[PDB]
Amino acid sequence: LQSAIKLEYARLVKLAQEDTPPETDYRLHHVVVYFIQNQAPKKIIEKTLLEQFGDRNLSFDERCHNIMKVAQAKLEMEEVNLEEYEEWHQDYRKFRETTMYLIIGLENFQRESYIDSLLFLICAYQNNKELLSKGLYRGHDEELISHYRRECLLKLNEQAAELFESGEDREVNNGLIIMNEFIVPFLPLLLVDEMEEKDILAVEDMRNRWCSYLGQEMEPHLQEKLTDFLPKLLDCSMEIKSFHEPPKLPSYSTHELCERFARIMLSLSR
Ligand SMILES: [Cl-]
Ligand SMILES: [Cl-]
Image (cartoon, rainbow, N blue to C red; front, side, top):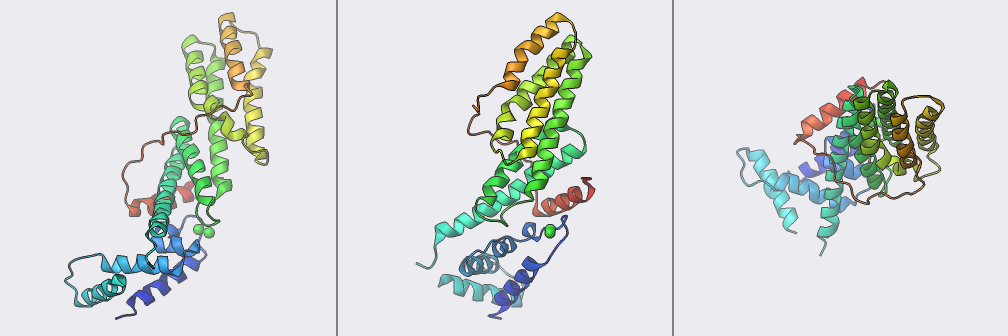
């Protein structure tokens, strides 16, 4: 059947146009769905379909063997544009990893493991902005990732402040280590854009919280600690390293990707 590829392409177009609830994202099921929703050239899509049919070497199924030879025939026929071809498949692999960062970030947020959550959400947010640079359908819901990155910062800040309010030397030092390790270094990320008003207000809310302890009386060696810390939190400088190493992802199957995405989207309460 010289048209099995045309049948399959027409099926994926239909899948690509279906309206689906937030837990279901057929871009995670097939690279060609990602391509269709992102206006990939018809030729990029056909080559991807032909290679999915024609890449194998062996078959025990007469009908599939024949479809394999047909696809290998068309593929063997300047029109290749390999850099464009590799670029689209790299973009899809980045979409899958971005999804996996987001899932682990949201899973840990829901478990209230905010230290583990935060870096995944920050990485997901930044990768997602890089995807959406290239088009509207390249990535994930910006307002959702924006919401959880911001709420995860505020909850970790709450955790650090309540440690500080306890007034014990170990807990104060631990709270200040949280602020200096996980929060202060990423404050510039939430100030980059004046249009992102909720992020601006959240940075101001975190800064007010730590300043309001000036209005409280406490052990003076702790007051010296607060006094050295506050300039760090209130600093005007936007100095931030340009590359950050991403947290480690455990190996995962596409099956895991899709199912864990569905499961966290369905249990999240926002
Ligand atoms: Cl949708
Ligand atoms: Cl959806």
